[PDB]
Image (tube, rainbow over all chains, first blue to last red; front, side, top):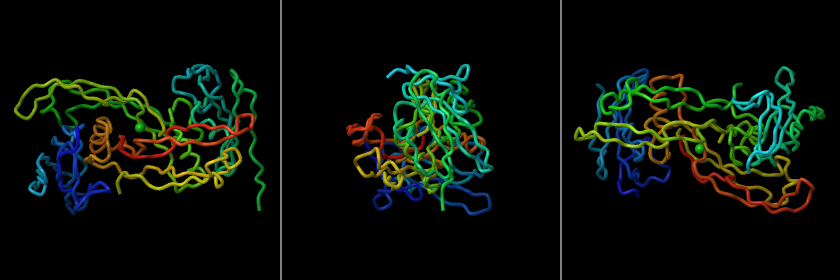
Length: 85
Length: 90
Length: 104
Length: 103
Ligand SMILES: [Cl-]
């Protein structure tokens, strides 16, 4: 299946991204991540279709907490804004 | 190519080696190398056919003195006795 | 100094938190790959020409990394999961289980 | 700094192979290196396994991350000397990294 979907990407861009944009056959993502001492930072990019279900499902307990959201419409991820539970 | 060659193996045995032999479609090897405390070690095993050109040859100048020798008959690496290259050097 | 090989790894769908979109199985043996890729790369590490050259270069230039112990043969498993509109679908997942490791 | 392809030229003269490899004098081999973080973006061609393993890592530190490795590779030709020393033309597979991913 061919790439058909455009997503914003911000820390996970492919080297050849265009205007901070990636293309994919999977889903756009946007992620919120806390570190070990305070600073929380935001990420987004494209998820390949294969294994998209394990990456767009919501975990219970990593080392420091984070959340991730996916959608399937062009540039749909600046409209996502995930928060920590 | 199917493996057709039987060799002895010492630290480089496959996890399913029996009686310290392994099989391959390339060559058998024996190499001596030096560790940082001057202790040397004999290793030996099977090299796949692919890339055997490079491995059997080696680089004359690795970071740790070593010597690898290859041969191509059943169990032949029992008869190989590689030695360290002289530290010849200025 | 232990060599590239397969290690056991069981994946409990509960530990990782999929207990609720995945209905069957509860886990599976997924295994994983770990260990040194030294010189020489023996036959059973299924190395590419690249990886062999890379190991040779690393040994002369420490700035170039060694080859990496990774799965060189993978296999499939099927799962039953509850999809978006709470449907129960059976689906075949490729590349889920390591059957073999190698230096690459 | 995430998994990607980096330059690497292998000069046969530098590694002492110049005396059984008659040509080319060297080649661009490239290599792969860098982190395999979560989530694994599309341009890392990850396998389902590398992905499962990546999640398992975030929850059990004893389980390593996916590694960054060649993921597509191309051949090159060389002129070399037979075990018996003399010009021979061989196609060497998987000599050149075309792409990298997390596996
Ligand atoms: Cl691979």
